[PDB]
Amino acid sequence: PSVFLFPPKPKDTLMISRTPEVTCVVVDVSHEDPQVKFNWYVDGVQVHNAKTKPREQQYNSTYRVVSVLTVLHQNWLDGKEYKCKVSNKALPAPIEKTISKAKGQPREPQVYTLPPSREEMTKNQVSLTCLVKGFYPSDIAVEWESNGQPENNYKTTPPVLDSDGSFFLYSKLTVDKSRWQQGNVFSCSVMHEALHNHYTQKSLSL
Amino acid sequence: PSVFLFPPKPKDTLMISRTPEVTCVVVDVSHEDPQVKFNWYVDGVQVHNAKTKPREQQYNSTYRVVSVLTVLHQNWLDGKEYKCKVSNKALPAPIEKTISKAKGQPREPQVYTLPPSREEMTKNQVSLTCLVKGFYPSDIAVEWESNGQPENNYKTTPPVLDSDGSFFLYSKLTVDKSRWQQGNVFSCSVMHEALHNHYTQKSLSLS
Amino acid sequence: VVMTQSPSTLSASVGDTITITCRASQSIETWLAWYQQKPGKAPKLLIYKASTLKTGVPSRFSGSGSGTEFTLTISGLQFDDFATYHCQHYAGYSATFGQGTRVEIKRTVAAPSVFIFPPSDEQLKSGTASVVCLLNNFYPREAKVQWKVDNALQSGNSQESVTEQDSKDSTYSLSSTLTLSKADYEKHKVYACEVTHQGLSSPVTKSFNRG
Amino acid sequence: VVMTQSPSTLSASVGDTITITCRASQSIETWLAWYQQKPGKAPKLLIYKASTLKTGVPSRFSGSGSGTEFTLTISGLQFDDFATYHCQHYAGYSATFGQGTRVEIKRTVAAPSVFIFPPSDEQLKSGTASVVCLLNNFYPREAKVQWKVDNALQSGNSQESVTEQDSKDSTYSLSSTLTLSKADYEKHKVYACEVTHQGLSSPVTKSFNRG
């Protein structure tokens, strides 16, 4: 067996610092039917071992021979098609799975930050909100900061399809009403393909 | 032969007037043995039927059989469990599926209205936000209204598991910047098990 | 600017008045053109600046709109008009096109009649094996064919071809050819073509056993 | 304006002083250049205006002549100098070359040792049969291979490849591959490679019978 392809994490393809990767996961491989082989194809080419690396199993009573391929930020962003071609004895035929990034003119996201509600100013903690809309495709990375340092207690809703075929989401940072009172400045970081330098940063404070 | 269990919609069990139901769907019932038997259980009881109600259909090259069990708002809200048992002669053993509301104590949702950012009111349309946090279970319903009528250009994010273990989401209503300025007042209605009459409401204006 | 046409396939009868819509993601004033294209031929300009008919184009073609919403109207469809229509925003240096709208002759839904053909031994003697699947007389044009060899789902070893609407019954037909060497062909027994189409309630499989 | 270079092949020893001639069909003043070219590489300019050495070119290269008669002299051949040399008349907007002179290491005449190899089984199972003939360690370079199938001369179904002069013994080797489909191969009995070479007073044939 049972194959599943996975696309790279958005943040990985937007910064050369990190290495993107197409992860091919195969589940429920039998004890008597191991020996799992792989084959990666990028736009047809490469039938013979490319720059792959797969290993590790053991499960509920089955296997799972997960292969991993290093992606070129450009390659992926330009839309090259990645094809994982698994091959197993206990498998009727050679299964397959392909994938490329969502097609379509990319659209730069709008980032707006919102203060906590007056009504929420009655709790020992407040909600810093970050709105992000108008972006396409949906791959996106959102983070928070305070004067150079990272914020941990935040949650981000997944991408949702708006009326115009674009996506939007909201990120929510939970902070002590005091820190918001002291006038500290928080910032919403958004990583996306259509942003200049694949990155924009918006601030909020009392 | 596959079987999928579907729970009633969030509003169905919150409003006594609505009709909440649990639906059992069976796909891929071979053309040869189209016999399908349903058995329903509410906390393990009812091998002997109940409301129940099946129909029969045909598709690609298989059969689809749907059975519908109407439930009692309080049985659902009281966490009762519903079992659908599907027996088919072309099946090694019967397949059973069970569903109910998530286990956990009900937390009241906090609903706040959030006006647009100064930097957005420079566009023809703005965003009126409605924050709903700290609720549980995730079953919930959100809506918008400006005057005695629904606003239909809005979107709600799906619920998100907070650090609390409670749930939170955001609904974004999009209004012509011209309207928001005319002093119009909007409001989002949130329906939840933990709200007074399963319903609260918050207003938002430009004052 | 992104241009979107509606619908993607427009089905109508001869003599009908039909409208194709084109929307721009942002205002483009009236900088919008419409082209007609027949299969294997060059696009032909019909209308430009939203509503100006190119000299020589028949008067049954008309265009309207400005800003973000545009329409091409064909008032009294003739057999010559069943074709693809493309809208285009053209600017000083670049241009952008809609996805195209195929205008086809409407008829009732028809499921494909499916046939599989083994390779001839005459060919097989030469060292190649072509296995052919025919999907005959179906409508609408969208269909899916997959090949299985000894129940193994195949990938990347087939090609497909589709006819234009049949002149008598307005259906489409499709051929898929699975190509293997003689040697690879003789390694396996069961050859099967599996087909889906909206007109079929379940997939249709045709098969033969080698030899 | 035709340029005639002589000789076509020049065989010499390391350290030799050699001359290559170019004759023009009419006077070209001193508008002549000389180029060196190694197999698979680009030509490199040595000399222009008949006698001017390009900077960096070793002083052992020299050129002379004017009118219709031109000479390239290499005074003390080094291993690096074994190569093809080309003369060129160049004008403002056109040029023409001689046919080239291949300068090689001289050694005694050596007859090729000839081997024929059938197609392997592995391949024959796939639908193709390739038959290889080898001409091993011969000198000089010109050798003719003629393929015969049931004593019928083959044409346009073979390709040849020749090595560069062996570093130790100064011979050449040649491989010729004849290519037929399993079908075509299985229609005939005897397969033969027929070799002509300076070292062979009579043509040499190596054969095998199919299977």
Image (cartoon, coloured by chain):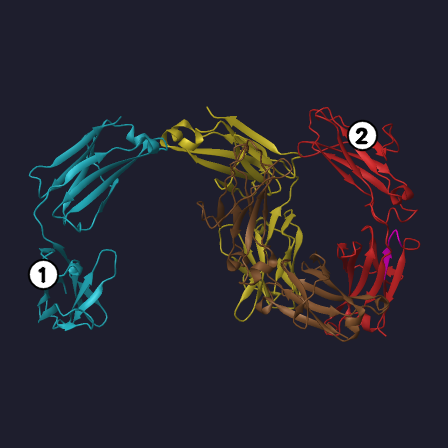
Chain colours: A brown, B red, C yellow, D cyan
The N terminus of chain C lies in which quarter of the figure? bottom right
Q: Nearer the viewer, residue C163 or C154?
A: C154
Write down the residue under mark 2. Answer: B38
Query: Which of the chains bears the disc numbered 1?
Result: D
Decide whether residue B23 is among the magenta residues.
no
Q: Amino acid at mark 1?
A: Gly
Q: Are marks 2 and 1 in contact (CB under 8 Å)?
A: no
Write down the residue under mark 1. Answer: D15
Decide whether residue B189 is among the magenta residues.
yes
The image shows residue A152 at horizontal and vertical percentages of: 70, 62
Q: Are marks 2 and 1 on the same chain?
A: no
Give the quarter of the image for residue C25. Answer: bottom right
Which region of the structure is painted magenta? B188-194
Crowd band around label 2 with a 10 angstrom C-alpha radius: few (<14), some (14–19), many (20+): many
The image shows residue C126 at horizontal and vertical percentages of: 36, 31
Query: Which of the chains bears the disc numbered 2?
Result: B
Q: Give the CA separation, mark 2 to mark 1.
A: 101 Å
Give the quarter of the image for residue D120. Answer: top left
The image shows residue A78 at horizontal and vertical percentages of: 53, 58
Left or right of C157 on screen, residue C98: right
The image shows residue A53 at horizontal and vertical percentages of: 50, 48
Q: Is residue A99 visible?
A: no
